[PDB]
Amino acid sequence: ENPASKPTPVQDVQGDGRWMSLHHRFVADSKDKEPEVVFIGDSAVQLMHQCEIWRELFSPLHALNFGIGGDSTQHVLWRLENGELEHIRPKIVVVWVGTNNHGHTAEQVTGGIKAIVQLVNERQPQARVVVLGLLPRGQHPNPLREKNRRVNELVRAALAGHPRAHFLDADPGFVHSDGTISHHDMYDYLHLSRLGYTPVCRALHSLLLRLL
Amino acid sequence: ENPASKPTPVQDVQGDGRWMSLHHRFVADSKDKEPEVVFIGDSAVQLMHQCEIWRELFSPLHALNFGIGGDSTQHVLWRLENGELEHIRPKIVVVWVGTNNHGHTAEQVTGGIKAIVQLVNERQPQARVVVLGLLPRGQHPNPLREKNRRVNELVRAALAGHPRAHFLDADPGFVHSDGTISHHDMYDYLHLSRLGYTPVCRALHSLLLRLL
C-alpha cells in the first residue's frame, strides 16, 4: 500500500469528535443540495470560505466547500468514498490537498492525488477535475519547498494526458528573489492571508468560468 | 515537573521552521516597538488579528499580537522567557492559552497558566495581566468541554486574590440548550468565525478600556 492512497478517516485522539462532525455536515449538504462545483481539500480550501470572499466569486457558481484543516490525501479520498459525493451531480470538482502528508515521499503524495482523481472519475464521471498545485511554505528555503515542487512536477505530468483533468499552478510568485515569503501573504508562512487569497482565487475563478 | 509549566520550544518535526520564524518576528517587534498591550496565546489570539477586526478595537490601543496556532501553556511560557518581553514596558498583557494541552489534566493546565502569570509578574511587574477563559468546543457534549470548564474554575479561584490579575469569561453562550455549538459561531467547532469573534472581542475591549 501507498499510505497516501489507502482511504482512512482521521482517528480522534483528542475527544471532541470535530473531524467526523464536519464530515457528517458535508454529507448532509450533499443530500440536500445540488452544487455545480464541489471544493475539497485541507485548510487552504477551508479558509477560502471564511477568509477570501467566497461570496463574490464562487457562491454565484453554486459551490460547496468541503475543506478540513489538517487533512492528507488519504483522508480526502475516504471522505469522497463515504458520503460526500452521494446524491449530487456536479460539473466540476476542485481538489487541493497534499502539503500536510508529512512522512510521505513526493512520489507517494502524487499517488495519493492520482487516486483521488480516479475515484472522482469513477463516481462522478461527467465532472471535470481541477487539481491545484501545492504552494510554497516556510519563511526561507527548506526541504518542504522542494518536496512540494516535486509533487507539482509529477502531478502535472500525470494529468497532461487527461482530457477532462486540469492542473492549475495558482502561485503568483510568493517566493521572492531573496528566498523569502512575506507574512503579508501568508501570516504563518503556510496559511494565506486575505491578501494572499486574492490572486489565487482570481486564477481559479478564471479557469472555472472557462470550463463552465 | 508539571509538563505544562516546564518551558520548551515547539520542536520542528516537519522541516520548514515556521514556529521559530514566528517567534523571531515577535522578538524583533518587541525590539523595535513600544506596545501598551501585548497579546499572547494559541490560534484564538492569532486569528483575532486576521479575522476579527483587530483594527477597529485593538490597534488604537497600541497592541501587539503574538498568537501562534497550536501552542500549549509551556510553549507560551518559553516564548515569554526567550525574547518576546524584552525591550518593552506594556501596561497590560492578555493571555489566552490551554485548550491545546492534550494529555495534561485540568489541574496541570491550571498550573501552566499560573506559571505564565508569575513570569509576567516577575519580568514586567508594572503590567496588569488578563487571562481569558477557555472556550467550549466540539459540536456536541464531550469530555474536553468538561476539562475546559474545570480549568476555568481552577484559574478563576487562583486569580481571585490577585490585585492586578483579572480573569475574564468572554463566552456569550456558544453552547445552546440542545447541547450544540453552531458552525456559524465556530466553523470547525473550535476556531471562531468572524461572527463568533465579535462578542468575544467586545467583552475584552470593554475590560481593557476599564483597566486602561
Image (cartoon, coloured by chain):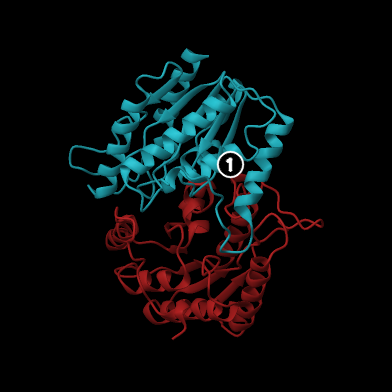
Chain colours: A red, B cyan
Indicate the secondary structure of the residue bearing disc 1: helix
Q: Which amino acid lies under the numbered mark 1 shown in the image of this protein?
A: Arg
Residue at image coords 58%, 74%:
A166
Asked if residue B138 is positioned above or below residue A88 in the image, the reply reads: above
Residue at image coords 47%, 64%:
A41
Asked if residue A21 is positioned above or below residue B121 in the image, the reply reads: below
Q: Nearer the viewer, residue B142 or B197?
A: B142
Chain ID of residue with mark 1 = B
Left or right, B9 with respect to A180, comes to left
How packed is label 1: few (under 14 Cα within 10 Å), some, or many (20 or more)?
Answer: many
Q: Position of residue B94 (x, y in %)?
A: 50, 29
Residue that protrudes farthest toward the right in the picture: A177
Residue A47 seen in the figure: yes
Residue at image coords 48%, 61%:
A42
Residue under numbered circle 1: B79
Residue that protrudes farthest toward the front in the picture: B1
Q: Position of residue B160 (x, y in %)?
A: 34, 21
Residue at image coords 20%, 43%:
B179
Q: Nearer the viewer, residue B108 or A15?
A: B108
